[PDB]
Amino acid sequence: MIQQETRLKVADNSGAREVLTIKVLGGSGRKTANIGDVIVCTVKQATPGGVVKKGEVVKAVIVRTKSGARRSDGSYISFDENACVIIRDDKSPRGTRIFGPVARELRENNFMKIVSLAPEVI
Amino acid sequence: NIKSAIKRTKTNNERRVHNATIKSAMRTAIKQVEASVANNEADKAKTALTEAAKRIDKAVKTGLVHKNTAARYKSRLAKKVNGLSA
Amino acid sequence: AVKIRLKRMGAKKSPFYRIVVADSRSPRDGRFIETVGTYNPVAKPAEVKIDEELALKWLQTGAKPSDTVRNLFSSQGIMEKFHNAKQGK
Amino acid sequence: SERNQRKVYQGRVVSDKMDKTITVVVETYKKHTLYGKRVKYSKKFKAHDENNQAKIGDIVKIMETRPLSATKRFRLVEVVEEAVII
RNA sequence: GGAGAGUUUGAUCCUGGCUCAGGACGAACGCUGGCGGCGUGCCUAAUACAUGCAAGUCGAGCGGACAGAUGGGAGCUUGCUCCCUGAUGUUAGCGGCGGACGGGUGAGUAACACGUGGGUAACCUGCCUGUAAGACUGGGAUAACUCCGGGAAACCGGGGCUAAUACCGGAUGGUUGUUUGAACCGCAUGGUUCAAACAUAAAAGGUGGCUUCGGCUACCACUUACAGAUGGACCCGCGGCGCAUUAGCUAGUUGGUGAGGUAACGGCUCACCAAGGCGACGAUGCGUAGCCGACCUGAGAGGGUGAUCGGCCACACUGGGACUGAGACACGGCCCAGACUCCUACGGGAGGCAGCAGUAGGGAAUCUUCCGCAAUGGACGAAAGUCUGACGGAGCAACGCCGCGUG
RNA sequence: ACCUAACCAGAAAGCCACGGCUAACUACGUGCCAGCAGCCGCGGUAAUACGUAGGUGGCAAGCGUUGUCCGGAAUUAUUGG
RNA sequence: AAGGAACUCGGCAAAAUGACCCCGUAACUUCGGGAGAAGGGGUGCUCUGUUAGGGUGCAAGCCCGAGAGAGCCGCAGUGAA
């Protein structure tokens, strides 16, 4: 439920603070992207010492939404803050740590590095 | 990686427990004789002065008192207890 | 207490103590209470003269020697004669 | 058997508005370590007027007491010279 | 105990700067390079760290536990094991002390931080002297030890059992607090000394040796009271720095009263009251910086630096916090948070080289991952001893100083 | 460590400077080119200044360059403008 | 719901902010402002408590009441306009 122009706060030590969406990547196409969905983005605000700066267009990956993650087993994951982790052209992240809890559905994507770098994968 | 006196760490835990029991018992007894000095009670004033006195010297005479602070506490408590009973 | 013991001094080839009275646990080449004595190990051999007029006040005013301080101050006639100070006990 | 010589220099009366502490600082001389010529200067001080019987502008100098307040060190001695007013 | 010379001019003198001769380093670089002795060697990034050692000790405190001379009985092998007693030796845990000294580094801080000089009728002091009293009567615990358990580990939990120099009642004790009677003297606070009532401890320890086996005694201990000594704590005078292109600052601030607090006065912290206080004699603010004995230089006044040795302060990955203790807000102790690394069974754990070396970075720039408690100082001991990267030494570098040589 | 005996002169000397300040001089090459330099300043075919060679002078298991501090600096002056 | 100006010539429109008390408030200036700048915190009830203190009254009596300490309960304390 993260369509175009949705300011997602970042969840790593890559330098960034607020990420602005541009286009969800799937297809012609779509207008929503729930959890684990790669987005083309920019960065509106940043911690001042960072390799990814303000005004730089680097892709990202959702981790958490206030929208639900719907596991196929009845239970629903839904966080209270939106998220991003920033990717450099392959699914190894540019970040170093990944803050906060993390939706476990990323592991069923190809993000097996991103799961290992993140504390509470639930 | 503590080389020696890790058992000093465990002795600081157990000694901190027993010392907290005696010292906190002294503070609670001092509030007890102070509470008995709160109201105008004669016989509880003198016997409770004996209670906070005996527990006071028994606390300051071993460990964390030590001497001058105990004389300050028993002195002011003696002033209030001597006030409420003459 | 103040353990009146030795203290190194001299070159790196030969050390010669000059055993001033010192604190309980001061540094080795550091602060001392009130220096009285000097006694090199060598030269020739072991010639050192001590105070005994204030050093009796130091050894009687609450103190003790080291090993070499006890053998030296027992050799110069100060520990025994101080014991004759305590012989009027 | 007296050994302690806690003594204070006699100075004028600067102000007594601070209640129970009428403090004023007296002036001594100094030599300038490069040039040589004499240059004096004041040195302020609070003075704990216990009776509060000081006069502002009356030269009375008192000796230095213990730490009595936040930077009030000298006790009073006597009103040595009264103020001449009117 | 002090030396000047060059350089403005077509020539001259003044005035005026600019440079050189001299010394010095914690130097580096260029060339070269025999030795010895004595000192010196991360000054830049308090940057991060692989690996080893840097604080242990007490069997003469404790209850074990194991081995075991020597002795005992069995089976066989004519030499062995099996089960007991036991000199003896060893140590995991409890407890006492020591990790607050020692070692390192200048990150901080422009004031009580340092130096100096007073003061403390405002403090405290374990260990050690010396004095003199005491060490009486009891209690219930608990780690060890096992039986189950949960954990990947780190590790926790629960049930049974024990002891001490562990802890905890009572008597006794003033001196340790509260009330009174005084006596003497001060620095406002008040201090010193005498008496009379209410409270406050003790390892009966251990070691030996002796004995009548009741007990005796010495030594090393335990407590209490005193003074001594060693240490730190506090307050204050004075001194040591660039800036006015920093003149405002301050509201727990200035002062009172009251209460609480600490070893202790104190807005130290709070309640209530008042409106104070600091400043051209430089407040505040920016900057920089550990300070001193001292070192280098100067004829001297002065100018510069705070290496190595010492004295004090500070800090211990960053930032708080408190416990144990006499004493820390603790460098190789804990709790929390942040950073960075390592482990992971993803539930959670582990770390602090500004100790000695040592590696990477930084840079022009700085070394051996060595020997030993023989000395001196420590620590623990009854001592024997153990630990001691302090120290005593060594290894490298012409890095400095001095001596000798290459005839 | 130091002592004693033997052995062999055998293995053990370089760095900077040579106009002035400042001890220390001539030749070849170069010809405002390459260069030096602390300041003064040299070098445009006779260079006591650039390199090279002999010699000299300083110093010595060391010698120069640079960094910083003091003096010279009476160029912060109280001494002393 | 989730996202918030991507709708649109244009935040049109709606949503939002708002009452007192207190803290605090910049550039700029014509020196008055700006400035309700900005940005924040408190409020409901019970008791202490015929509070402190005022107005009024001879007392009785009412009114007008800051400020605080304890405590209550709610998602919510100018609970609404």
Image (spheres, coloured by chain):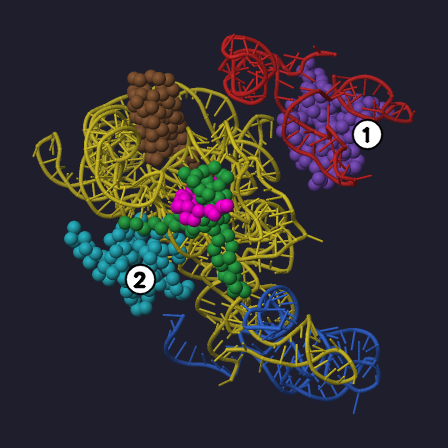
Chain colours: A purple, B brown, C cyan, D green, E yellow, F blue, G red
Q: Residue at x 69, y 24 (%)?
A: A81
> Which one is in front, E65 or G74?
G74
Q: Residue furthest front?
A: D86
Q: Amino acid at mark 1?
A: Ile
- Which of the chains bears the disc numbered 1? A
Picture coordinates of residue E202, whole percent (x, y): 25, 32
Instruction: Compare residues E285 and E398 and report the one nearer the observer.
Output: E285
- Label 1: state its secondary structure: strand
Residue C10 shows in the view = yes
Q: Amino acid at mark 2?
A: Gly
Neighbours of disc 1 within 10 Å: few (<14), some (14-19), many (20+): some
The boundaries of the magenta stretch are D64-86
Mark 2 neighbour class, 10 Å CA radius: few under 14, some 14 to 19, many 20 or more: some
Going 71% across and 21% down the picture, which residue do you hit?
A66
Which residue was labeled with disc 1?
A22
Write down the residue under mark 2.
C37
Question: Which image quadrant is residue C58 in?
Answer: bottom left
Q: Position of residue E344 (x, y in %)?
A: 58, 31
Q: Is residue D82 magenta?
A: yes
Compared with D45, G72 (above or below) is above
